[PDB]
Image (cartoon, coloured by chain):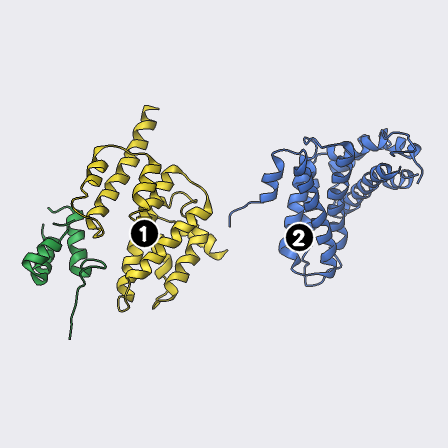
Chain colours: A blue, B green, C yellow
Amino acid sequence: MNAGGYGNLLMNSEQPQGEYGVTIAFLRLITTLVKGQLGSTQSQGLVPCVMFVLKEMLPSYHKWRYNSHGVREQIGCLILELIHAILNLCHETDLHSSHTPSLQFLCICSLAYTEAGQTVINIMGIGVDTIDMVMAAGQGQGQLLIKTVKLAFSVTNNVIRLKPPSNVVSPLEQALSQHGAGNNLIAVLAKYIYPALPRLAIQLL
Amino acid sequence: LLVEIERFFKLHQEDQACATCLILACSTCDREVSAWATRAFFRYGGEAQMRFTTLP
Amino acid sequence: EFLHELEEKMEVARIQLQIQETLQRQYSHHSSVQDAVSQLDSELMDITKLYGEFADPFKLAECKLAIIHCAGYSDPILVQTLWQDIIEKELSDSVTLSSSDRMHALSLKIVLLGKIYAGTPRFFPLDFIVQFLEQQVCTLNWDVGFVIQTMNEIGVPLPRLLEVYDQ
């Protein structure tokens, strides 16, 4: 028909309350779907489309207001997770070119082109400022924070290696140098050890 | 009678109504409504009323 | 805004003219109940009044449909339910020989109403309607293109029809 992701329009209007729940449910379903592609079914049509929503979500993320930062933690982590998975899983699935590469390709081009670091930076900043608290970190929140941060670092990491074969290079690398560390990333390892933080941060560097 | 042509039908008869209906359809300077209606009567008669037919 | 009032008026007035015209054809009516015509010509009427009083009692499904267009009543169930009645009524009059004859009349009835509503999607759900029509006509002799041709004639574009149909 003619172009139209219903979920995007419906969700984008506002992001408090149930609307957040709706988006989260979608993201969870979408993520399971990519995993499902591992098993495989009619992957190719659904799959790229999933990224389209995911990518819209990730950059729209900056502006959106969330119920809470923890909520924000969950959404960013999962959305980013889907995009991370798409790049990685793509090779394994068998038909021909791949069901997923179209999906994955959109991912690479997206960051490769109009590049908004802010979603990535946001995670970097949040992780920097978690509360040094034993409880209510409880470690459920803490685990989410590490998870968003870890997943984000790995994801940025994936982009960078993937970038030179194509030899995109340029801005993402520069942006990473800017954040890098070059101040905030370096700080990250101090915060936790790696109780969450250091290996991922160092690995990225 | 164009809107009810039963009255014409009653007095004049069906055949004559058909003939006049044909003339109106063909008739020149007539409104489209008139021509179409007359054509409709000629072709289909009155729906669920007067039927237009060969009978054994 | 004057224009706003004027156009709405023209629309409602037109409906009465249609209802009035049908009243003549209808044989359920009595000449002495001329009062209805007097009422029709006499003034503009409330839409609900037109709908409840005239359309339902005289089963003018087409009119009812058009009226709800102007009202802009979206409710799909009610809109669809009305459509079901129109289709069902059509079946009653038919005899079979006029598969073609009915074919034409059916297309004729649909196209006319279709032209008026087709601009808006609520009364004329193209997606919902097409199958409905096919299903109806299916219990009849068939030539391909009979269903779609009516929509094209209705005023629907080839491009619009194509995407929905493909879907």
User: How many labels were placed on the picture?
Assistant: 2
Chain under callout 1: C
In the picture, the disc for residue A100 is: none
Q: B47 or A90, which is in the foreground?
A: B47
Kind of residue at disc 1: Val
- Residues tagged by mark 2 and mark 1 found on one chain of the structure: no
Which residue is painted at 24% across and 32% down in the image?
C43
Judged from the image, the secondary structure of the residue bearing numbered disc 1 is helix
In the picture, the disc for residue C111 is: 1
Which residue is painted at 67% across and 61% down in the image?
A41
Q: Is residue A182 visible?
A: no
Residue C65 is situated, as x and y percent measured from the top left of the image, at 36, 45
Q: CA distance from mark 2 to mark 1?
A: 41 Å
Residue situated furthest left in the rendering: B12
What is the quadrant of the N terminus of chain C in the image? top left
Residue A24 is situated, as x and y percent measured from the top left of the image, at 70, 42
Kind of residue at disc 2: Val
Relative to A161, say whether C101 is above or below.
below
Residue B36 is situated, as x and y percent measured from the top left of the image, at 18, 52
Q: Is residue A56 visible?
A: yes
Residue situated furthest front in the rendering: C32
Horizontal arrangement in the rendering, residue B39 relative to residue C91 (left or right)? left
Residue indicated by mark 2: A47
* Residue A141 lies in quadrant: top right
Relative to B8, say whether B31 is above or below.
above
* Residue C91 lies in quadrant: bottom left
Which residue is painted at 76% across and 50% down in the image?
A85
Horizontal arrangement in the rendering, residue A194 relative to residue C69 (left or right)? right
Give the mark toward the camera: 2 or 1.
1
Chain under callout 2: A
